Amino acid sequence: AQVINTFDGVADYLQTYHKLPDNYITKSEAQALGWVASKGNLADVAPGKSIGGDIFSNREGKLPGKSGRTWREADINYTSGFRNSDRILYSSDWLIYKTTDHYGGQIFVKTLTGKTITLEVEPSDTIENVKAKIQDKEGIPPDQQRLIFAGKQLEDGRTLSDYNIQKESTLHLVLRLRGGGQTFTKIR
């Protein structure tokens, strides 16, 4: 088969045919074949395939937004091993963007009701930015959010990497009732 997996090649193909090349499979298709996120076994169970076609939420607004416009992503320059940091982003109206610094992936967050949600994050995300994403996706105000990981409370100002949180890690929301709005701290 002819693998199209470059920024330029996938971009042109997407623009010409309005679909991904044949070497792309969705995460669920990959999961069905045995791919386990974080194990780097995609090419073992699906030689010559790359992950692509799934919804990209754009919760940080870094891509141009518009009513009715949704975004999808696909892996770029992948052959085998762990997925890399290259992605192409394409909209329902066929705008095309690229990133070479997508170092993140999904984590899980266990809410107070018992429900567990998934959230796309980067290791460089600050804690206060993660709380905003939880608000954006689940509707929980940041002032009701207290996040624990492996016995340690996640503090505003720090990043996920400060706690070695990574793909597939699980965060735990714990009860916070004191409410409150914005708070300020003196910088001496």
Image (cartoon, helix red, strand yellow):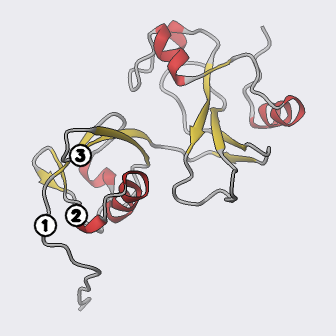
Amino acid at the residue labelled 1: Leu
Q: Residue at x 64, y 39 (%)?
A: 72
Q: Residue at x 29, y 81 (%)?
A: 182
CA gap, disc 2 and disc 1: 6 Å
Q: Is residue 87 visible?
A: no
CA gap, disc 3 and disc 2: 11 Å
Residues at discs 2 and 1 in contact (Cβ within 8 Å): yes
Write down the residue under mark 2.
Answer: 144
Which sits in the foreground, 21 or 124?
Answer: 21
Quarter occupied by the N terminus: top right
Mark 2 surroundings within 10 Å by alpha-carbon count, few (fewer than 14), some (14 through 19), many (20 or more): some
Q: Earlier in the sequence, mark 2 or mark 1?
A: 2
Write down the residue under mark 1.
Answer: 177
Q: Earlier in the sequence, mark 3 or mark 2?
A: 3
Percent coordinates x, y for residue 67 in the rendering? 68, 57
CA gap, disc 1 and disc 3: 15 Å
Q: Residue at x 52, y 23 (%)?
A: 27
Q: Is residue 73 visible?
A: yes
The numbered dot on residue 111 is 3
Amino acid at the residue labelled 3: Thr
Q: Earlier in the sequence, mark 1 or mark 3?
A: 3
Residue found farthest to the right: 16
**Quadrant housing residue 85:** top right
Mark 1 surroundings within 10 Å by alpha-carbon count, few (fewer than 14), some (14 through 19), many (20 or more): few
Percent coordinates x, y for residue 151 in the rendering? 10, 48
The vertical placement of 19 against 45, above or below, is: below
* Left or right for 116, reference 146: right
Q: Secondary structure at mark 3?
A: loop
Amino acid at the residue labelled 2: Gln
Percent coordinates x, y for residue 62 in the rendering? 60, 59
* Left or right for 108, reference 33: left
The vertical placement of 125 against 9, above or below, is: below
